[PDB]
Image: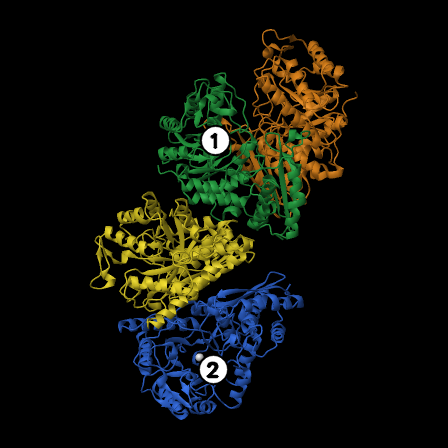
Chain colours: A yellow, B blue, C green, D orange
Amino acid sequence: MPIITDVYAREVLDSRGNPTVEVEVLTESGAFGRALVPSGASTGEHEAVELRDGDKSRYLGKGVTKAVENVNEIIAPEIIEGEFSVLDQVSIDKMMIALDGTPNKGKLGANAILGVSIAVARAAADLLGQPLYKYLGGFNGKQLPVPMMNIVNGGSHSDAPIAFQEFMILPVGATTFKESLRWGTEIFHNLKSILSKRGLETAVGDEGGFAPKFEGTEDAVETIIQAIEAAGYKPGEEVFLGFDCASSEFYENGVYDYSKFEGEHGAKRTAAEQVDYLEQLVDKYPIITIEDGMDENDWDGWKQLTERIGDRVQLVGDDLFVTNTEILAKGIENGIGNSILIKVNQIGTLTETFDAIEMAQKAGYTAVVSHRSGETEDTTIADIAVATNAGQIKTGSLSRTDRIAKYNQLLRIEDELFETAKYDGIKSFYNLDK
Amino acid sequence: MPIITDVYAREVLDSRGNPTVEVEVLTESGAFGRALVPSGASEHEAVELRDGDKSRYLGKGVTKAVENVNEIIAPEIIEGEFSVLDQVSIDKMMIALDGTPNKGKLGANAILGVSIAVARAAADLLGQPLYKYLGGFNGKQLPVPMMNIVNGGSHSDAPIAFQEFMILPVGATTFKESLRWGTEIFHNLKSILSKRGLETAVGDEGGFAPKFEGTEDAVETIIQAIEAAGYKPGEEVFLGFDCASSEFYENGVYDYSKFEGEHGAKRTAAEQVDYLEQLVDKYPIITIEDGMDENDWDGWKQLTERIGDRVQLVGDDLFVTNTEILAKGIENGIGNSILIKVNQIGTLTETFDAIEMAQKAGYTAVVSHRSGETEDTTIADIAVATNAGQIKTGSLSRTDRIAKYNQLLRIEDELFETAKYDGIKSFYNLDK
Amino acid sequence: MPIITDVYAREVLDSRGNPTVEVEVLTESGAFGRALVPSGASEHEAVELRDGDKSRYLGKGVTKAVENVNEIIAPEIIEGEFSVLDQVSIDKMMIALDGTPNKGKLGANAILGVSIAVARAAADLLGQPLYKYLGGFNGKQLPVPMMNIVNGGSHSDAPIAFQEFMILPVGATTFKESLRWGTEIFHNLKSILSKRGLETAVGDEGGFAPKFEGTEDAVETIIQAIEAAGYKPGEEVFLGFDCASSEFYENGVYDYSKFEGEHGAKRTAAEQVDYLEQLVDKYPIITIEDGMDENDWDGWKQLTERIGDRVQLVGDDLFVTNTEILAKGIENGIGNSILIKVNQIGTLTETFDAIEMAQKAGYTAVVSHRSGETEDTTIADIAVATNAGQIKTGSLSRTDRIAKYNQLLRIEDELFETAKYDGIKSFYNLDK
Amino acid sequence: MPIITDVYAREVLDSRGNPTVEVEVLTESGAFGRALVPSGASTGEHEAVELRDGDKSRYLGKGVTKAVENVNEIIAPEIIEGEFSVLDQVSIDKMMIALDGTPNKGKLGANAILGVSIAVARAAADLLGQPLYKYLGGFNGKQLPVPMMNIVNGGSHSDAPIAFQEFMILPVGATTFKESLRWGTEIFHNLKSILSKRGLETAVGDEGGFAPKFEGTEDAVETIIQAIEAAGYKPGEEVFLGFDCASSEFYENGVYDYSKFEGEHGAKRTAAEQVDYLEQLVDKYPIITIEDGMDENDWDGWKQLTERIGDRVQLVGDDLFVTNTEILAKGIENGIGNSILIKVNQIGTLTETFDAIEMAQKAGYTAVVSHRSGETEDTTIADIAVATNAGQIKTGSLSRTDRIAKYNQLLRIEDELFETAKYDGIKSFYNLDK
Ligand SMILES: [Mg+2]
Ligand SMILES: [Mg+2]
């Protein structure tokens, strides 16, 4: 029954219109799994890199035929001839890491390897008749994540004078994930009206949120607040706010240079002034989470920021950790941050992904599983959040199926869990004292 | 074994963030089907059921529809011991159970959910690809895609009357190649827009709504993106419109001033035809959807006599996926193509009847998406099952659209050397 | 197929010769699970049900608990048609069926028996090793074992206050190697004791209770056995205590005179901390269990501030595998590790919640045996399922202990090249 | 279905902390059996010898990697390539005896061979859906054994001035095995109190019984009696006593030298005086069984002892017979003893074990299946006693799971047998006239 008999990859498209890898796994008894890999980075300092073709005359160089070939001609024959059972996730993942033989995964491609890794796990779940989350996390996978819902974009994703890349709402005060999703959409739609009445742009970006021409950061925040209240919810209690500052995008030579995005008179802040500024914002607005508040290399700044607001505010390393456990470990040992953004394709296997989540959790950090800019109809990250009782997810705004499909999968998971389902609300932030 | 043992509905979300119905069907032997219903309409149209509870989802909840499946439709199926393979008796039974031509008591969305999920479960039981279960052994023709790229009319702040502008990669050898071109043209257009300082964020169907100066600006810029990607506008890639002329038609006149400024022409039926013929003569346009008002039957006649031999004329608002109205169009020689919106008629059986009617009249049947979509890909399989030759399932952005394209890629891959992509020969309705 | 068709309990014996509960679960398809319950306690603790019939087993019979399974719990499961895979709903249902927080109406031992046997049967149905069914695909980390070797306090006639002395073979490469070392050290100690004319018979946990002269004699002799076996006390093998200080704590004072003669120090909270720090500075001690009284929260704070960065401080009596109390310890920064006794909380679900809480607070969760054990090996699989990193399951003597060790050997063997043994890195709770 | 497809051995630990062999057998249809071998002797005169590694730097020379290798590299390939069905116990056992080719089993190791032998039988029982006892003994295996329960130790297992190695209680007067076990524990626990009140040692030895510092043999016996009575049972009727004298341990040159263990003034008895002494003890105390009352080589003494008390007292050869049927046969032909201790690993296969039991039974002797000092979680000897309607077992005191697990298995066997179960009490001693 469980021996893997076929592993097949093909070229398909992601939510941005760019090629990506899809892999299908079949066992001798006919259990089946399909995996679609989200967009990645083909160059980087510390992450698994995906393999692109570079053929300027197909898909503007973004085709993934090489990665597809590597699956079909290198990985699949090793798996088939090895007679691996679909249940041996870790050996298969370890075999693929060694077969690529680079820390990068850049010989075979992180996209090739991950497609296989997830396809196998899904096939195993199908074979056992298990919901994926329980196969991945065992019998006690039951906690639905509080979602970080992208609502407004800035920085390099906007023309408006705003340095922070993304603003989010978090419906922590709901009692079920189902309710939390509802609130999200109500707030989203109310915001759309408000923007439309103001004559601002209503079309959406990659994450399915808005990038309107606000006057600045406070305009943006306060308008979100207004949308929360207009929908009938309370900002301090039921719905909270979050940032992805992506501060690396505007940091150079020890200066957080807000004028890269906020125009001539934007503040040029030192590390100590960046912290003061974020503390001010947090004392003013009901902000529960900040991603990349300091630069990916400003560890002293991260330290300062963690010492100052880390007891009562979640601080998420994205560019800081890059889903790398050697870097996460150094962060943990130095008391920097209290949360890590887990991007599955940035590390490249399910096994390594679960090791990062476990490492994070065991240090009292939160592990927030994350979408990419180019997503697919794959809903695996919803199952991973519940499998690990992660307590949080970041999978986009409240439009576009590349985002909504994950929310739908969470609805199905909560439904199926029935009376065993758990939604911890504010207690999901176990990384926080106050 | 094929007897249906569970029919279960659930409230989920569509691509616009509004509630829709999901239905799951199981047979005694463990075969499984899931359907999600696209966004619809709450005359002459199957209607979806919305809750109207101002405190939930702004009145757009579908708990009553979900409840109609679980408390009314499911027990009828289950107690009736219907086989999962008896698609037509199940659909028929649901139409009778609802009792109104509207499908308004149970909801088109309750009914269609079941209808699709039953078919998918049948395909699962039989080990068949869905397109082959639906269409028989000969379902093998991949559609030329109508790819939305620019929006106007009420979907834009720009002074353009027509609602959609489309590209059609007819000249490609395979569906796979044609999809590639779509994306390359689309990405070239994107960077041309940002180089002109125009807006790049997308709407419901994953396309652009840029502030162009006018209809000629939009078209000419689409053409330039096609050429900047290295494809020939006359032969490899054609253009298409959805004018949605019903939107700017008031009191016997096509009032472009509704969307196109203060000096937009007020146009008579004869002047519309002239303008459309002008555009067709001045640009490589192969299809026009709703070029005339839904009730301007005289105008439709005129337009079909004028350009029908060489341009596809698609009724959307004109036929509303209603076979009574389609029959009348055919009998009176109006149009040469019909947009099929599965949730607008409400069953798979009626959808296939509607397609069959169209095809037997020498019309093309263009299976279509809705503004609010889902992760569901059934419309891809319908297109191939009926060798329709065409599909309209959005731009090259948003998984709500791309998922359908991806499913066509899997279908073509699976079909291997039996797969067919006709290109310009897909337009069997066109005398030219 | 996964529906539970039989739940059956039976009176058997534990490793001390006292009655305990055995439960067997069967599914429709023939999948099978057997659990045996370890010895417990008849406040803030799940309680086991004892018969109290002075004419049977000296009042320790469990016929009423067995009867609660067979006449009350089983029919609820069977009539409810629970799937064997629905571990959390079954446990939840049993908690509600009992109704008291104690688990005192049905008995923690009735409930836990069912809970474990259901999981084992699920693992059997799925063809999965139990650690993988319980923990998901990534359960692969073998625990460093806390190996009891010498006993004191109320488990010895010798003048020693602390109840247990342990070795930890942290420096080993594999669990297999670490188990080997345990046995070699233990057998070397045995012959050193018989060469000194000291007692060699073993207690409940398979260790020794020799009449040493004092606490320094015991420790120094353990170290010598470690060195006589060719291992380095500082790096390869560390020591550990279970002081069980609650035992000699009266009226605000740690009264070593309870066990340590007539001139054993009466010690204040501050003087306990000093002494413990002294020992830690003078010997390679990596863990202390219950170094302070179960109710001396101020003292625990003090001790954790003092040595918590570099010594593991385990609450046993302090937390009583109760998440309300654990939460408070975490909130107040007391301890850095919790002893998990599955029968002290009473379900697998609550056990995993308790472990999860601990791990998420940066605490280690040390799965534990009880004085009265059985041939059951589930705690081995729990340790690996949760990648706990540690286990406390006895000395290197008695199958009640060795069976668990043997099961860890099978687990490691089965895991093959995926198996992990972290050694000193298992102490992720320790800043040093 | 029944063909053996895998035979696998590994190193595990016994109840004394020493390596032993564990073997697992699988058939093509997935029937499974696991066997753990108890401690043996690696040298001997007349027994199967187990194979130890002799590597002084692993497990102090007691590792069994060689035996494990022999299973995996010699026995398993013969079984797999031979395509033996799991049901052909005797051919497989005969094949292993010949493959080792020595009377000792010392080439491959008695531990290697037995592990396989039992694993196969268990797999066969699993394959057929049969309780093991019925597979081994056919449909009429239904008699629960009267247990010989170790309670007090002496001789070389004690510092106290007592020559006899072990003292036992036998709850012959109970009506079920279940009840008989209860009585055992009640007596055991009562004895523990009494000893504790006397200030004597309460820790346990290998068999889970006591080795306290009694004044001598009578002190020991009478204190056991006291514990019987204090628990509410009658010494002459419900509970009887037994010995393992292990008289070989203190015999030399025709002298039973009690001073080897009972100090300066211990009696030095001739063979005729040993018999008188045992007869005296039996007339004084309710002793129903004596193991190795005479030396393993003192056949004339054994004769004398059998002629004198053999009609009314059970006399068990352990060191005398060494589970060897050539020696048992000579004993039977010479009228020596009336019972034999069956140690499965001393002979080395299940087949040979059943031949010894059958030989014993057919001579009107009793066959008492026995534990070893180093035991395991294996419960096979419980099934063997019932399979053969042996009527007696010797599997230790009433503590330690290495002992209790056998008692538990007997409880399960009795339970499952239900109304067909049989516990003969005193009539189990069919070898006795009076
Ligand atoms: Mg239209
Ligand atoms: Mg303790």
In terms of image quadrants, where is residue D228?
top right
Residue A420 position, x and y percent, is 53, 52
Residue C288 horizontal/vertical position (percent): 43, 31
Q: Chain of mark 2?
A: B
Mark 1 nearby-residue class (10 Å; few <14, some 14–19, many ≥20) = many
Residue B371 image offset from top left, x and y in percent: 44, 73
Amino acid type shown at disc 1: Met
Answer left or right for A259 relative to A285. Answer: left
Task: Name the residue furthest right.
Answer: D433
Which corner quadrant holds the C terminus of chain D? top right
Residue type at mark 2: give it.
Answer: Asp
> Is the CB atom of the residue marked by disc 2 within 8 angstroms of ligand 1's nearest atom?
yes
Q: In the shown orientation, is residue B149 left or right of residue D409?
A: left
Chain of the residue displaying label 1: C
For the image, the number of numbered tags is: 2
Mark 2–mark 1 Cα distance, whole angstroms, equals: 80 Å
Q: C12 and A91: which one is in front?
A: C12
| Label ID, residue B317 | 2
Tell me if residue C237 can be seen. Answer: yes
Front residue of C290 and A334: C290
